Length: 268
View 1 (cartoon, rainbow, N blue to C red):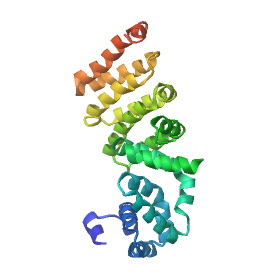
View 2 (spheres, helix red, strand yellow):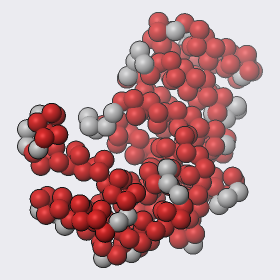
View 3 (cartoon, helix red, strand yellow):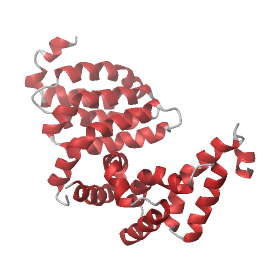
């Protein structure tokens, strides 16, 4: 209620949910009977089982832990949580390991290695240390990952700067994909580029490099359509910074000049 008096929220319970989202990772880190007691108190006030509450976030919890946690500490915390929840922590993963991959990939840019370990553990449950095996694993999950990115974009609650970080992660992901998969996901890549274009004057400065990738990361043989879209989007981007756009253009124009033939014809 105090934090509420500082944060002025209409209904104290929705404000409590706001708090609880952040609280849950903290509780996970604790993995102590007293932490379970705090959670039980919150749920008692919440009217929702603290067990089921801990459950609901277990998915986000895994991601943020794997990113920032001690592996051994991770397993200890997971078992502690499971016992209270009455659900095996592993059994819950069997239901949302794909969403976990989505999360990690979201944070993959900054926690590349933690993403590795998590996705590997999940692949084991599915049926990885090698980068190519990690990729093969990611390929089926990344469509839903993109879906999650767009879902976040839709939500007002989600932060936009967070979308920017995720966009950087997406540059990393385009790199990791390789041409075979970048071909399949080119459309969604251009879609994400659009989305980011929606937010400007902060997203432009990173999204320019994002687009440089988007072009090069995209397969060399065909770039006309995406270049149409890109010149379109970039003309506005130029006003923010003239040079990044031009660099993106030049990569296509010269590096893909043989393809750029009749592509120029495309857009005057």
